[PDB]
Image (cartoon, rainbow over all chains, first blue to last red; front, top):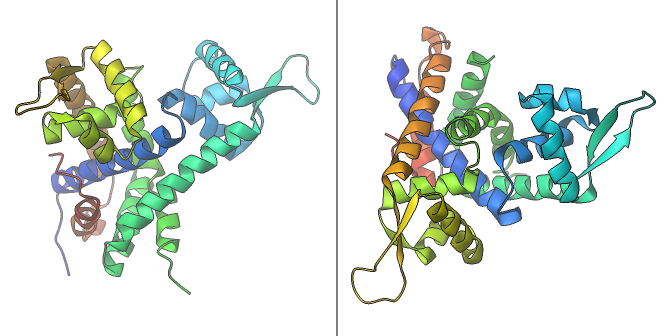
Length: 146
Length: 147
């Protein structure tokens, strides 16, 4: 019970602090695996894990980046041996990007750190709060973007 | 069986995707070059004041060698000053620079603007029981209020 109602402002403030705790969790996870990797780099890695081999055009669209800056960065990650480039089945031109075994290990290690840290925090919460938290973040995800 | 945990944790990896992307975007929009661990370092510094490397690394949950390296970088980028230890020591303290504080403030204000825009879109009917749950999350996680 009950609450309520809750104003935008108090909901936003609570979500803001929650967002800092999730960044803390991510920072811990990313740094443990790769202390140098950037935001757009890791996002690229996750995209490829989630969608599998895709052309640079498609990658760029999902990244929200210009195709030109995507090529440069893909190349860096190729040099870090996290991404391979593959011929299309079969276009000219393109050209598809996919994770190396290494790229895959990066994404899965970061996830495993995140879930261990989350689990640790969740153990400290009452079962009813845990459930309420899933509800709260799901509702937020539903509302926008959406 | 139980427990699981765990099932909740999994539901949470999925449920938190958006907030995380919004957070990551907000950092990236102020400085293109700052990593997420780097940004967390700055937030810890605004919350904890000047602290030494051992304390920073522990609060970050990152290995000290790597922590030391990312403080060096942030020093190079004028976001962090190294200060003398108040008592004895030997070890130098790390603290925010004015520009450092602006970065933290800017990223925070921009993320808040995106969050509230999305909160305006939740039906008034469903605006119940949200704060309680979120607050329990941050208390359990030890995260200070944003504010």
